[PDB]
Amino acid sequence: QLVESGGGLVQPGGSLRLSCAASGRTFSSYSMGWFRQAPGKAREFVVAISKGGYKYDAVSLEGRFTISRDNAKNTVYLQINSLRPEDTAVYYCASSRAYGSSRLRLADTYEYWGQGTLVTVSS
Image (cartoon, rainbow, N blue to C red; front, side, top):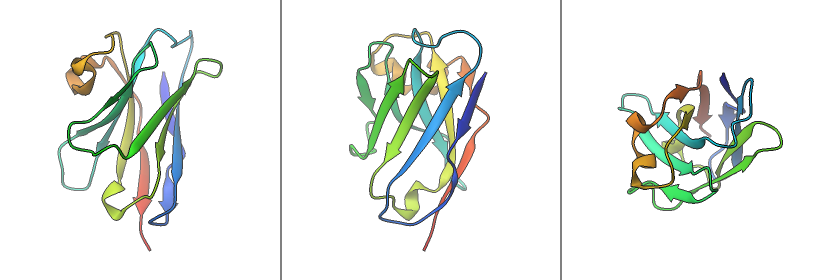
């Protein structure tokens, strides 16, 4: 149902956008989250956008990610300005029933998961 795209090898300091398309019926009533697994780490919450369109930042990612959705294309986007080597990870998209709250920061709030897409930041 969810298929991410946009991954690849990108330069530090530049910006990059990833997409997540959801298959079948409209996803406008899902909250959508982005999660990542860096090499060697446990999964980390990045940012979420509620059904309402409100942004939920992580507690420790320091306001560096910007999320938007396109209910007119099945698509939520993740934006990373000024990519740093620490951004390297498999990025997963996920969809939740839940409403905007501090629960959208939790991986267990999400029912549907993408297939993943690799972002590699390197000079």
